[PDB]
């Protein structure tokens, strides 16, 4: 019955992907950012320059105050608000209504984005990273406890809408086989990267470096984010491969955007990136390959040029690897919480390089994969 959920997401990589939800009685409609990197369901509940609408607890007969405050910091942005519960539904999701925890956001900093068209956030990860603590049941945990919806969801983010299939896998959204990697621990959607190659060349780092201090799958982050040492090794490699042309160093910091005459972008000089993920059987892994069309994010020209301009969508991290939206775009990603694994497959909405193709390939053999986990 998943066909009704296809295309239930709007938005872009750089603006966030959001789904429509309703809260309260009578139902109030809000667009909610879908975020696998956190575990709090929160909505603007007070006026804000960037909000065209918000949650009004006074208008809902089913609202219940929990008389407790809450604060949530992200890599960027933060808000504080008031905990309560209310009835929640997803119009283009399963046909159910659940009582869910909701943080009513009363104050925020660098959280809401001007003209993003969303007014809240849906944290899809586990209770362990919920604020104020893990006793605040996350939305998806509530959905699964209160209804018959199976304990999984999948995401198909399409670059330049998407689909969130709640409760299953829709086989028409991907081609080829699904490959699965264990969820290392149920807090973030944490996985283990066991090898990295660039244009077929092994970075040859201690694989612990790739997962220092963790690696997570996050639909709510735009970029691929890498630990300092890995980020430096990657950028060095990508520079050398594209040394044909000259780029400002502010470009490699994701600040300045480079441009080319419409339809003349030299994709071929940028390397593919292969991330190998721990697999499901002993000494086995598989790889996802990223095309430049993914880590060069298209942006509006700062001038009156009909040129194609891009930003470098790989950035340095001090909190581990983040596989963000630009990586998830062009894969179908299955968050199989029931079997503690995450699946990847080539998306039906993948980008078309002329001579290269984004791919999910296996099996590969990799000795000692356990040693790649950071402790
Ligand atoms: C409370 C413990 C869990 C905290 N989890 C995290 O911080 C995750 C690692 C990151 C989150 O997934 C977090 C959720 S979105 C918060 C809004 C930012 C405005 S910018 C945000 C929305 C527009 C598109 N770019 C996005 C982005 O790129 N956000 C990164 C920068 C980020 O921060 N994402």
Image (cartoon, rainbow, N blue to C red):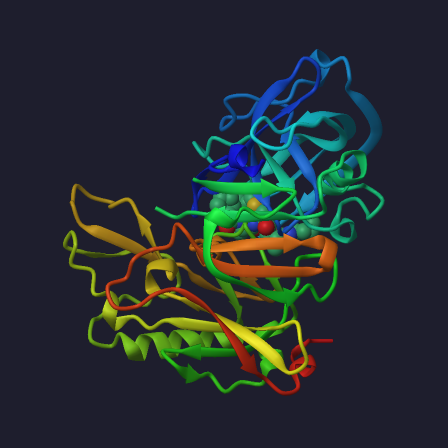
Residue 285 quadrant: bottom right
- The answer to whether residue 291 is left or right of residue 260 is right
Residue closer to the observer: 163 or 16? 163
Q: In the rendered image of this protein, does residue 141 appear above or below residue 194?
A: above
Q: In the rendered image of this protein, does residue 195 appear above or below residue 14?
A: below
Q: In the rendered image of this protein, does residue 353 appear above or below residue 80?
A: below
Quadrant location of the C terminus in the rendered image: bottom right
Q: Position of residue 10 (x, y in %)?
A: 45, 36
Residue 341 appears in the picture as rendered: yes
Residue 87 quadrant: top right
Quadrant location of the N terminus in the rendered image: top right
Residue closer to the observer: 340 or 34? 340
Residue closer to the observer: 232 or 288? 288
Q: Position of residue 304 (x, y in %)?
A: 16, 41
Q: Position of residue 332 (x, y in %)?
A: 50, 54
- The answer to whether residue 182 is left or right of residue 164 is right
Q: Residue at x 62, y 52 (%)?
A: 37
- The answer to whether residue 35 is left or right of residue 39 is left
Residue closer to the observer: 30 or 131? 30
Q: Residue at x 69, y 12 (%)?
A: 59
Q: Position of residue 31 (x, y in %)?
A: 54, 30
Q: Residue at x 75, y 47 (%)?
A: 130
Q: Residue at x 63, y 87 (%)?
A: 367
- The answer to whether residue 141 is left or right of residue 160 is right
Residue 54 quadrant: top right
Total numbered labels placed on residues in the image: 0
Residue 77 appears in the picture as rendered: no
């Amino acid at each position: 019955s998943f066909v009704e959920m296809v295309d239930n997401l709007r938005g872009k990589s750089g603006q966030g992907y959001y789904v429509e939800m309703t809260v309260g009685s009578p139902p109030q409609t809000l667009n909610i950012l879908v975020d696998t990197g956190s575990s709090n369901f929160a909505v603007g509940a007070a006026p804000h320059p960037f909000l065209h609408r918000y949650y009004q607890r006074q208008l809902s007969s089913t609202y219940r105050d929990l008389r407790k405050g809450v604060y949530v910091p992200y890599t960027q942005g933060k808000w504080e608000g008031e905990l309560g519960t209310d009835l929640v539904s997803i119009p283009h999701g399963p046909n159910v209504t659940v009582r869910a925890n909701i943080a009513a956001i009363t104050e925020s900093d660098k959280f809401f984005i001007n003209g993003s068209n969303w007014e809240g956030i849906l944290g899809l990860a586990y209770a362990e990273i919920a604020r104020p603590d893990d006793s605040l049941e996350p939305f998806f945990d509530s959905l699964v406890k209160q209804t018959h919806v199976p304990n999984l969801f999948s995401l198909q983010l399409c670059g330049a809408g998407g689909s969130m299939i709640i409760g299953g896998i829709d086989h028409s959204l991907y081609t080829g086989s699904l490959w699965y990697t264990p969820i290392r621990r149920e807090w973030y959607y944490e996985v283990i990267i066991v090898r990295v190659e660039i244009n077929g060349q092994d970075l040859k780092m201690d694989c612990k470096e790739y997962n220092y201090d963790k690696s997570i799958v996050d639909s709510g982050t735009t970029n691929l984010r890498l630990p300092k040492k890995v980020f430096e090794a990657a950028v060095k490699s990508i520079k050398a491969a594209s040394s044909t042309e000259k780029f400002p160093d502010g470009f490699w910091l994701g600040e300045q955007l480079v441009c080319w005459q419409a339809g003349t972008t030299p994709w071929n000089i940028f390397p593919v990136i292969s991330l190998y993920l721990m697999g499901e059987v002993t000494n086995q892994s598989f790889r996802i390959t990223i095309l430049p069309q993914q880590y060069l994010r298209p942006v509006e020209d700062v001038a009156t040029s009909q040129d194609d301009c891009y930003k470098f969508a790989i950035s340095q991290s001090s909190t581990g690897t983040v596989m963000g939206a630009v990586i998830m775009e062009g894969f179908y990603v299955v968050f199989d919480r029931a079997r503690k694994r995450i699946g990847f497959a080539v998306s039906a909405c993948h980008v078309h390089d002329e001579f290269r193709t984004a791919a999910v390939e296996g099996p590969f053999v990799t000795l000692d994969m356990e040693d790649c986990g950071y402790n």
